[PDB]
Length: 57
Image (cartoon, rainbow, N blue to C red; front, top):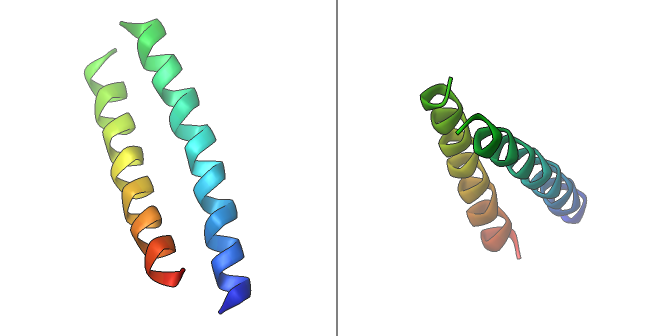
């Protein structure tokens, strides 16, 4: 379970980097609605991952 927690944290920070990169891409593209939807989906996945991490902690 501890190993699973660490894997969840690593996936959380990797997806955080991905969300920041996609948000920068959307800001550059401000061809925009699709990027907005992708960023919102990544943010929702990050929120679910953070909820799982909080439950694990």
